[PDB]
Image (cartoon, coloured by chain):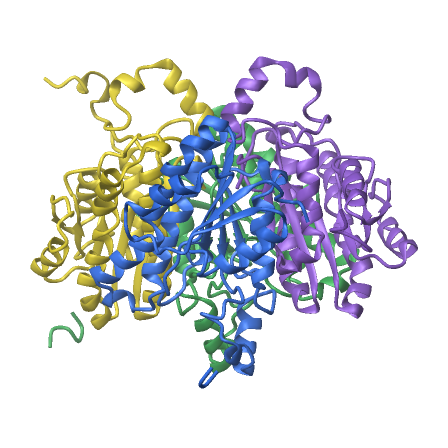
Chain colours: A green, B yellow, C blue, D purple
Amino acid sequence: HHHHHSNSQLAGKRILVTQADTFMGPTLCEVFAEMGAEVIADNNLLTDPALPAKIIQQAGHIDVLVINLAIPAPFTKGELVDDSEWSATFSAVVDPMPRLCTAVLPQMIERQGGKILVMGSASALRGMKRASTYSAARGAQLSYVKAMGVEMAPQGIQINAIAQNFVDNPTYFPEETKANPKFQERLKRDVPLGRLVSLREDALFAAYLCSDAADCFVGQVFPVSGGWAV
Amino acid sequence: SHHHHHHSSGLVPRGSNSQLAGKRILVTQADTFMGPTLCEVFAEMGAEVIADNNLLTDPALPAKIIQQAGHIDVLVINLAIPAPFTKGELVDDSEWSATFSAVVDPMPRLCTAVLPQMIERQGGKILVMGSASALRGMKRASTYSAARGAQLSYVKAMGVEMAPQGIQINAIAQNFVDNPTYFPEETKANPKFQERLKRDVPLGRLVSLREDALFAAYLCSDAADCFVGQVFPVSGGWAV
Amino acid sequence: HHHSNSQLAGKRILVTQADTFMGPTLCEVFAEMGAEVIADNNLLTDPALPAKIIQQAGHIDVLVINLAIPAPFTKGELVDDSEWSATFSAVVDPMPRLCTAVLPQMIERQGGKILVMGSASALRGMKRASTYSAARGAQLSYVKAMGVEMAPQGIQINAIAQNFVDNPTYFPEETKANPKFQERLKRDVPLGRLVSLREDALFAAYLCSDAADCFVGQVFPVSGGWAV
Amino acid sequence: NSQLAGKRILVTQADTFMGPTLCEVFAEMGAEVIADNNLLTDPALPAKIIQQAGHIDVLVINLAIPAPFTKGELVDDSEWSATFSAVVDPMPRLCTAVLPQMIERQGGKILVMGSASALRGMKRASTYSAARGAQLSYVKAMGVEMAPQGIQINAIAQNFVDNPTYFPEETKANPKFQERLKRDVPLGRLVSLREDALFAAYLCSDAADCFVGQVFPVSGGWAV
């Protein structure tokens, strides 16, 4: 009858989040701020080769760089893919990554500390139909992280990736899809978890990897896909 | 009067609240391998820790330990004996039986004992404290590696099976964690060990007990309900 | 019914449970490629039996550890000690007994191969296969460790991790011919068909060949893309 | 023997990386080898090479430049562009050119000669690793997609093969190289060019029709 009516994990870290208005940008910016980060949100698509170095320059001190990069994944049949689709996908998802890392690494190497987290795709880990261009781009991200993480670990710098799929992302899982019983049957068959990973669950895992507790993780890819890929 | 105060006075540990508040967590072999650190870190995050110190070679014992605990939110399957260093061509039944009896056979007894209450309420977690020796081959570890592989494969199968019942079954696969049993002070004080460690382990240092336990604490939290049937290597990049 | 090729030339290959799982096809294909095949038919629950079999066979160039019982499909929460013990006794415990019996001659010669016929159930989780998967995982982790350990002695220890192989035990003709099974298979297995017994055995034969001396402590999924 | 009897196999950059060994061994196994020696940075060139060949049973995508050794924090756009232009971009140009004839007859194979640097992190190889990762993830996706049309697309992911580009006699003779190699490579020696090529030949055979979208590490246990 009484029952009717009756965080600082990232405190003081300056965290830059790229394409902060799309893919996992909104969830990361919201949850990182709840956990005490100073969030630097940038909304630019990074097709412009000059823009990453300007965004990093202008942000000043960066403790954590979150490389959140995306365009809507092409559905093109693998035998029909053209140079325009390949360049649009790699220009947006792949080419900006080293540009962001080479801009931010000097300050992290100077202070022997810093983190870079890539918000990547489990499409790079497990093959699926009609996603060949996006999968290839996403594989370039994961292999870059595995190599850079081994390389920068001795400098006190942690470079890791999430490899996500079946996250509650409105770009791919709009409410009318989620409400469809054929969708729910497919999801339960394909995803052991039996539901989408929440935006909050994804960002809280990201927040753990951006925390002092995760200093032991270097060059590691973490699948987040409800068991679709582990 | 203790010597750690000369240089380690006034230092706040890595990751220093209520992440496991109101969770009853049973830790097996709580006095060995990762047990002590897990019990300390879980209590620090607000868990009610049920610490069992028994070696579980007795087939009857797992069911009795689960039975006496009543409600268990999280079962942490921490099973270990000193890893045999035996050359592969010299392994015998006594070594194989000793290792599997301690590390492998208790695992399903514990899970079959605790799963009924978890199935009935559609909630619960089982975390296996496993070994990256099961992921990546090393010399003179064949028996221990095989036993640790049984754990990880059990987890991947059971986690898929129990996910639809609202239960998360996962594993850590650790190596190069600072367990003084395997990395004694006399080893750490040897420059060739430090030089070899930086060669073989991308992190360039041992993973701290605390770092490993903080990751286990995350996996035991509500935030980690999205993880089912997943193995998480914790080895400073030695295995990823 | 109702009432009733020199790829392996000059190699002695012992195949365990030669009448069972991949045994028959391995024996056929290895013989086709010039191997002298030692076909042993014993279930190896008896601890003394692997040393006897290896002793009696004499010179072994390749040991193929083919171990199987019908996989339990017991719900994970209902598994008992009898199931666990029967599965590990058959599929796991014999493996080191066979390897410790055969390795001395291979170490002496600085040459030899051990190939485990394992399961992709150890790589990818599936429902209602907990005991069998755990046992198969012991096999694959044993191979990875032993392969690293014995490589410097000039010995190659590897595994196949199969699933969705055209084994009539698990995939009867009548099931294969069912259109609902054909739909599920095309959904779950990229290959869109079962791997033939011969395809599996031919890959086993490649791993047992001199060309495969570069492979040590490696697991090779053979499941038509279900696990890679 | 005749493991590849009556197969037309097109090998790209047939003069570079694994090209020469693949051409020798495939012909040894009874293939009709179509050797093309071009660097494929020109976007127009893959379609022309496939068009001129007529029937292709197997396409071997052997793409390489010497791997940059640049420190990760010092990589610039020209290194990134040069590596992806040579190693990545030509890959789908080649596949989109050959796949129509394969889809039409419901048969054919595409094998990518890739790198285990995409699987396991190594220092001073960030650009090359990223490029090689694009190849392996392309293969996994394309292999699933094309398997139902009766086409097999797979990759080798190699390292520690006896390739004189990376392991010249001077390096191999250094006992400090021989010490490191035995530390880092379970096999305890380099994989031979012939071993690598015979494995590739197996994957181009009818017996390997069961393999779709699969990556095969070939690195003496360095990556498995």
Residue placed most toward the observer, A148 or B51: B51
Q: Is residue C206 left or right of residue C160?
A: right
* Residue A108 shows in this picture: no
Across and down, in percent, residue D162 comes to 67, 29
Instruction: Give the number of marks.
Output: 0
Relative to C70, say whether A70 is above or below: above
Residue placed most toward the observer, A203 or B196: B196
Of all residues, the one furthest to the left in this rendering is B68
Across and down, in percent, residue A102 comes to 61, 34
* Residue B55 shows in this picture: yes
Across and down, in percent, residue B93 comes to 26, 41
Across and down, in percent, residue C14 comes to 47, 46
Q: Quadrant of residue A83?
A: bottom right
Of all residues, the one furthest to the bottom in this rendering is C2
Relative to C54, say whether D175 is above or below: above
Residue at the image point whose x is 63% and y is 49% from the top: C33
Residue placed most toward the observer, B86 or A225: B86
Residue placed most toward the observer, A106 or B231: B231
Q: Quadrant of residue D191?
A: top right
Q: Is residue D147 left or right of residue A184?
A: right
Q: Is residue A45 left or right of residue A188?
A: right
Q: Is residue B178 left or right of residue A105?
A: left
Of all residues, the one furthest to the right in this rendering is D52
Residue at the image point whose x is 56% and y is 34% from the top: D220
Point out the image quarter for the C terminus of chain C. bottom right
